[PDB]
Length: 191
Length: 191
Length: 191
Ligand SMILES: *P(=O)(OC(C)C)OC(C)C
Ligand SMILES: *P(=O)(OC(C)C)OC(C)C
Ligand SMILES: *P(=O)(OC(C)C)OC(C)C
Image (cartoon, rainbow over all chains, first blue to last red):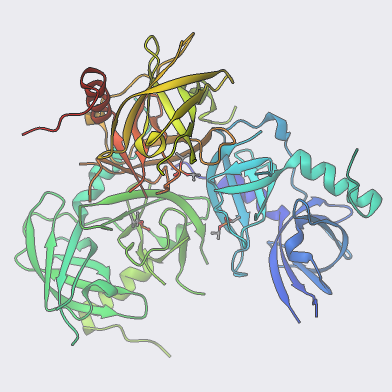
């Protein structure tokens, strides 16, 4: 009856996972949110500040299924990391959108795991586009605990939220980075 | 012409009252917001942290009419209290909605009395549903001064905002609690 | 395809300029946002806390064109000041709306220059209307760096944001003040 984001979120959530890290750096237990970017390979994109110095990475799908995961790549620069699910089965990958098509007045939605109690959704608009970090929005407060996905009304990934209003690495940037991790195990800066 | 919440708020506001407390605890003057939950009896639901240790409770309707009120019940647990208007006349009660029907992407509106200058309205969506406190939303910042009603687009009460993003006791929870106060003068926990 | 404020913002932005001050008070470099209120005269309205104690005022249009500007009036009271562009050419003035027509549930948009990296847009609704400062909204957080324009869905100026949720001097108030500066070089309080 009344307008709601519930419908689209019902399509997106299956791509959003929750991360539980147990590493060290001379214990230490961090926790975060992630997005399945490749269903067959089980490629989950996330914040580097969550999986950094991890000994054990655990992933849980919105349906409640739990999996193990391993690091495949990371980049302190953008706070973007890539993990891979162990024995992935029946996974749903988010569809990425063309960041370049983003306009400021655009409505965005941020999904995350701020307390480890599950997923939290917030809304806003694109505040600024083209300090650093390509995307800025009021849809996600600048929290060192707020990462996760940045999605548009069509439920497509426009960016990944990170900590330094909020800043997110735009999806095109994320595609380029992560894929670069898959092939090189790391992101090679240019010249 | 342009979309606005003004229309629905014009229907809801008559159910929203403003509370002015004057108690003690060995003066002390607190102030808050409330919602008329029963028009005939003049049952106004509110935050316990506002009416706690009250000697004198005063209520003012959005039309400007002032009334006296007495405590009927309270519950430190959920920050929910119930007061009753003295000699209530021509009152409007809010219609409660089924909390269980709540979905995250849902739009919500919070109404309150943050400065004693009148009512303040803010909007957001249901961030999280099923730490504690059943409802979480970005429509009301986590303020020890922000309580009041949590309403949906149809102008129905979905919860009462309280202090520990924001957390609200869902309406079904509120119904159960308050009614329990009416009959027992207090809320009896289970086993 | 999807609803967005981008269309209307595309019409409004040309009226929004960015201010760069270089004054003193025994250097000192401040920066802010402004709104072209008169295209022929090049009258730009802004916050007093930005142009106060200015030796040099510089303005840059959203298209990138830069201009010099001089003070014509100011008012510490409301944090409203008026500057005039030197040799103004092909300027666009914002259309002001009737503040008196404002209702609380109304959607608003705030435009500003919080970091000097360009314009930042945020959205919200009118929280409170009729402490001080006529307009209150969640569309602009209470920031000593957040000033700029307060606009409605039709892209009309309903107020100017200022620092003391957010507070803005309503447009009618702004019209009265600024015009009073043009004629008297200052705002003469009444009796
Ligand atoms: P975050 O900026 O905010 C939580 C702390 C409520 O946004 C998340 C949902 C990505
Ligand atoms: P609160 O969380 O915020 C005020 C301090 C602006 O929300 C009220 C309107 C319930
Ligand atoms: P401000 O209250 O917020 C920035 C600090 C993000 O709003 C501006 C855009 C007027």
